[PDB]
Image 1 (cartoon, each protein chain N blue to C red):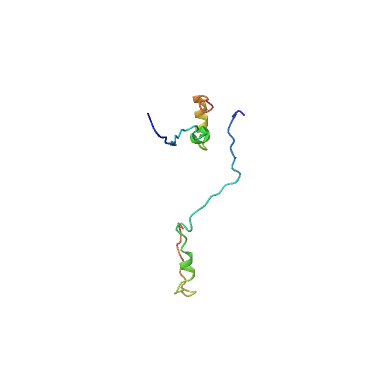
Image 2 (cartoon, each protein chain N blue to C red; image 1 turned 90 degrees about the vertical axis):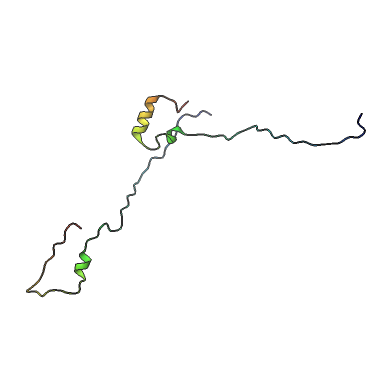
Length: 50
Length: 49
């Protein structure tokens, strides 16, 4: 018996994980709110960087 | 001159073998990096020795 080289198992797949929310968008706060303006006096939003 | 006898038994511990160790220098040094192994190959065949 003569030692010749070393064997290695080449990885086939790949696993990448990410955190839960990472500053989730406040869409949920605007969707299910408590006060909603009328149709003639509707108010928009400026949701950005979410 | 002795007049009787005394059959005694003694012990003696002597090592005859040790731990058969085997260290893979390809995994000890440069575990999974490719450029690390490329630079290690420049130093010669020390791992084979």
